[PDB]
Image (cartoon, coloured by chain):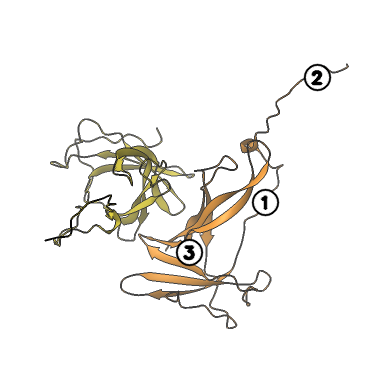
Chain colours: A yellow, B orange
Amino acid sequence: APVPLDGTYRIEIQRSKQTYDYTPTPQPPDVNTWWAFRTSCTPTECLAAATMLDDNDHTQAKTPPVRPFLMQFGEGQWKSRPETVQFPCVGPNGSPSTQATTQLLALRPQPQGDLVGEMVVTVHSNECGQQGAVIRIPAVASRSGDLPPAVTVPDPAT
Amino acid sequence: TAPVPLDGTYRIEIQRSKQTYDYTPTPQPPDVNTWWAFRTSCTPTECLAAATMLDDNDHTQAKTPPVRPFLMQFGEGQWKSRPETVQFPCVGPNGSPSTQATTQLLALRPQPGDLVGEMVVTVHSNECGQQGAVIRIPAVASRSGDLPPAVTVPDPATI
């Protein structure tokens, strides 16, 4: 004979505390993407461009053509341009919505030819109560071989 | 000859973003140079560094009164300090002085043994029309010798 639920109740869902049931693989899984990179260096500044490759086949360009990934080196790191991305979300009230975000990738080179850095997501609007929140996601890039013959990369300077 | 008279309402527009300094062979404004006594503590999980600020006239001495110890943490290929919430005076698009809420930090990327990076100032309020503006200032740090004997640095893991 449980005590009856009668009346107004506030229900509080503590999302910041959510956990996954143990599993020996990252949850959510990492996002792995393959890129054909090319670099153009003036004696003033360096730019790199990247064409996205297919996940089922790293020998082929991804179709339809993904916009070329532009990165610029400066102040010790590679950094892409902030992309203004809309983002679905759920507000503190349960109501689904969408919030405005800036996303970029920063990548810092290491001796052996690998890079380490992060993706940075910034929320600019407050539809879901997160205006001003900054999410950082660790990132690793490693060169796994040379350009695939079937794939062009445009000149970064153009 | 005699000029056309100024009579009536006039809008005056001052294009600050286009301000320039009269030529001078030194950076304007001048670089800010500051000296720091650093010490590092690395666990196999994460590394921290702390720094005591040294005196502007005499690099052998701690700056007084004691500046808060400069905390930096290494992660994802760089040294980064914690965002300091700093109020900043400013003038709005209307001329009225005011002050805006800013977040400031320093990021420093190590090089084969110097460091290079930037200070990042973010504006969080809109009293001067700059909410969301991000200012980046290039930064260079170089080790110019050892710890001065007259100067302690706290353990980074303290606090």
- Callout 2 amino acid: Asp
In percent of the image, x 30 and y 34: which residue is there?
Answer: A67
Please tell me whether mark 3 sits on a helix, a strand or a loop.
Answer: loop
Q: Would you name the residue on which mark 3 appears?
A: B114
Number of numbered callouts drawn: 3
Determine the CA span between mark 1 and mark 2. 43 Å
Q: Is residue B84 left or right of residue A104?
A: right
- Callout 1 amino acid: Thr
* Front one among B98 and B102: B98
Disc 3 is attached to a residue of which chain?
A: B
Determine the CA span between mark 3 and mark 1. 23 Å
x and y, in percent, of residue A122 in the image: 39, 46
- Callout 3 amino acid: Asp
Mark 2 crowd level (few <14, some 14–19, many ≥20, 10 Å Cα): few
x and y, in percent, of residue A103 in the image: 36, 44
Q: First in sequence: mark 1 or mark 2?
A: 2
Disc 2 is attached to a residue of which chain?
A: B
Mark 1 crowd level (few <14, some 14–19, many ≥20, 10 Å Cα): few
**Which residue is situated farthest in the right direction here?**
B2
Q: Where, by quadrant of the figure, is residue A22 drawn?
A: bottom left
Q: Looking at the figure, which quarter contains the N terminus of chain A? A: bottom left
* Front one among B66 and A54: B66
Asked whether disc 1 touches disc 2, contact meaning CB atoms under 8 Å apart, the reply is no
Q: Would you name the residue on which mark 2 appears?
A: B7
Position of residue B152 relative to residue B26, above or below, is below
Q: Which circle, 1 or 2, is nearer the viewer?
A: 2
* Front one among A138 and A91: A91
Q: First in sequence: mark 2 or mark 3?
A: 2
Q: Would you name the residue on which mark 1 appears?
A: B26
In percent of the image, x 41 and y 36: which residue is there?
Answer: A157
Q: Is residue A43 left or right of residue B2?
A: left
x and y, in percent, of residue A88 in the image: 29, 39
